[PDB]
Length: 242
Image 1 (cartoon, rainbow, N blue to C red):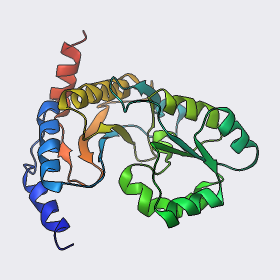
Image 2 (image 1 turned 90 degrees about the vertical axis):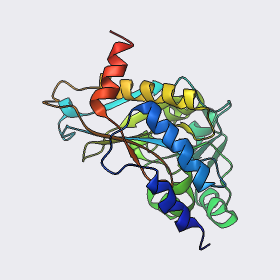
Image 3 (image 1 turned 180 degrees about the vertical axis):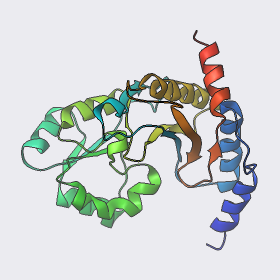
Image 4 (image 1 turned 60 degrees about the vertical axis):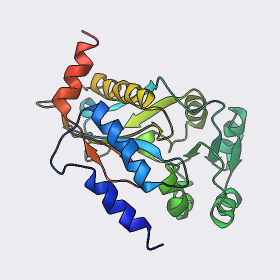
């Protein structure tokens, strides 16, 4: 498709390079970007924060959850990659699709992605990796950052079913949160974004020193990023609270 790349750079031209945007500006750009990108799946809206923490220490771990104000109409369809004891727990907890090598091969070979969230045990991730190419782009790859790689499958399934978004900073201090679909009306996306940003703000650990947030940006899965103005956003956020 000698079309897709023309579309990517056009969408990039919408962003002022070193410009740092308000949430309301950014969601406006995301929508304009999608107008150009015209993707055939409903792109996930992604929040990226880099935090000033070394999570090697317990007291600098950034970990939490938040029920975004606006999510997809329920029920949320949940796939769990699991074997043995964990598969039983998975289905007991109400997972829609529970499976191992067969499930994984069905997804890859039939290009079947009819579900809202994927969770995997740590033991299954090595087998799940080959799903990176179909799931990655659709925001469906199980990841520790979304807390979707775990042996505590029951709590992860229930959290997904309730729209509780889980986050966990990585070793480099980066948090990634999906905060809705681009198909959502903007007012909803702005709401979800304050909600998510506030949650990470409140997760500030006791060992966190100096300037907590070092970078913030929002993206669609396959679009350029929009940098956010950290101090503006935190001001807007504080002004609506205390």
